[PDB]
Amino acid sequence: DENIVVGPKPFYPIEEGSAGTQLRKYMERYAKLGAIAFTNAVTGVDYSYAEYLEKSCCLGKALQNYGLVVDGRIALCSENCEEFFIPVIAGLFIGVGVAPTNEIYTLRELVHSLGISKPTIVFSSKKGLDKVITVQKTVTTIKTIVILDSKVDYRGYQCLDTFIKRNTPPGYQASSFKTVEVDRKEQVALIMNSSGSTGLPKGVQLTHENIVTRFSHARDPIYGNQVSPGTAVLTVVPFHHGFGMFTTLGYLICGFRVVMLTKFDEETFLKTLQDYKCTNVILVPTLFAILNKSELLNKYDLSNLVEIASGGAPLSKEVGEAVARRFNLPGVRQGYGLTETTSAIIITPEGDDKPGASGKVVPLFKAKVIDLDTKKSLGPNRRGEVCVKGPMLMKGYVNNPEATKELIDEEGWLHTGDIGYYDEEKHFFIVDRLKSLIKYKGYQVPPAELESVLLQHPSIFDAGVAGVPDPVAGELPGAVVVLESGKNMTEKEVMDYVASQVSNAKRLRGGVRFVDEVPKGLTGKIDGRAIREILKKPV
Ligand SMILES: Nc1ncnc2c1ncn2[C@@H]1O[C@H](COS(=O)(=O)NC(=O)c2csc(-c3nc4ccc(O)cc4s3)n2)[C@@H](O)[C@H]1O
Ligand SMILES: [Cl-]
Ligand SMILES: [Cl-]
Image (cartoon, rainbow, N blue to C red; front, top):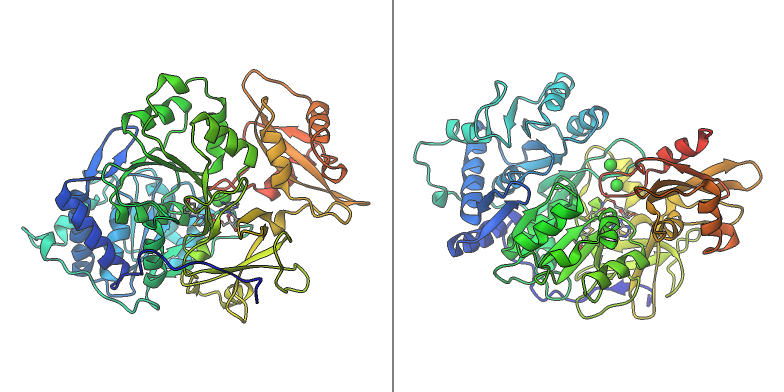
């Protein structure tokens, strides 16, 4: 079938050994070099590769001495912090599955998530502690809570350093520690949760084979970023999420300095770029609003920045192109993936640009676009559902065979739930989620296309679009808008503006509501249910 798009061979073949063995190999190289692995942009704290590797090895041994066996389970519950990956790496080193979660989860989300992954130990931030203690009242199999981001015991709980000290031989040498080999294709490495689900979180099981495949992409000269001392990546992406997890682990394989930024004001962003001589940025497109508006760019030395990359949510072509222009870059690089595909499976290839494109199929993957009704494959420039297949496909959801069957079909193709198309040169364009399409009469209007128009308005800081129920037409497109500081637009002004830029079908017949924050999930996808609720309330 000539409609199937097949990714090329990777420059670097997948290496032997577990994901833990590969991380240990590379981290030890950069440790001996003397390089910095993690930096907190706001506090300036650094962890060298040597320190990060040593603590990860020591924690691995500590978890074994505690009594965890291969295929056991631990979890994190933490906002981004520079210590986040110590339990992740330790788990990978010893064959103990790791379930990352974020402090920002609601209690309903967290109790469900940890109830599925069933961690023996939870590594909690100070901020997340109360939620973890609450969850433990329901998920009574959580034996121990360890404080991740404290150098001292806290509220009666051992901190990470204490847990390590109490569970290792005095004078234990990390250099003696051995990574544990596993059955790579079968052994669960991570249990992940997607953002923006309409239901409660499912546990996505990712294997070592999934992760070592990612490691080839991450360092690829075309589909990743190359090893080069002094590379510093400013990252704003949630670490617990696949987007933050697999970019960050990839950057460690690459030897980069991971410059973790948790404050998103323009001044801190730009100061961070300058002060740490950042070469790369990785973000969710929500951050572009600040960059296109900033009047401060030439106050900072931004000469080191050579790449801005976006993922997780639709990026307006025009917004991205304006930001690339401001930073004098050729374009914004992009990746597209799902938690269930480990990482990005469509990435903009270096040297193979196309305006508006999401990118091309990554090495070792295949992709097709199917007709929404017949499920048959489509040629170029035909919209339908993107389907993918390749060695980063998850093992399956935890204890949910029905959901697995719905996602990955009888021919092994993962149905992404996204609308897209590919052009004659095989560049893929991801439009929006199928579930988000607004059924106005016989049209299927993608909110992202209307959101793009709204974001392009200089008085509109943010926007989200969803469908208002309508007896005659089914659904009407409506918008929730956040105005820029000091600016006003009426509902009519917004509607008339949009009407001047779009087809008749795409008019905001469902109206406009003004809010302080557009409801979105943790990686920037619009919360359609929440938007519909706002639009339903009378002004
Ligand atoms: N680039 C994109 N454009 C438009 N939509 C995008 C998108 N990426 C994710 N999405 C949306 O998120 C949904 C998946 O949500 S999710 O489960 O929470 N998972 C994700 O969003 C997810 C998991 S891994 C990942 C990426 N890894 C990367 C590595 C490098 C890079 O430069 C960019 C990326 S994005 N994203 C998709 O189905 C799609 O709707
Ligand atoms: Cl989201
Ligand atoms: Cl979310």
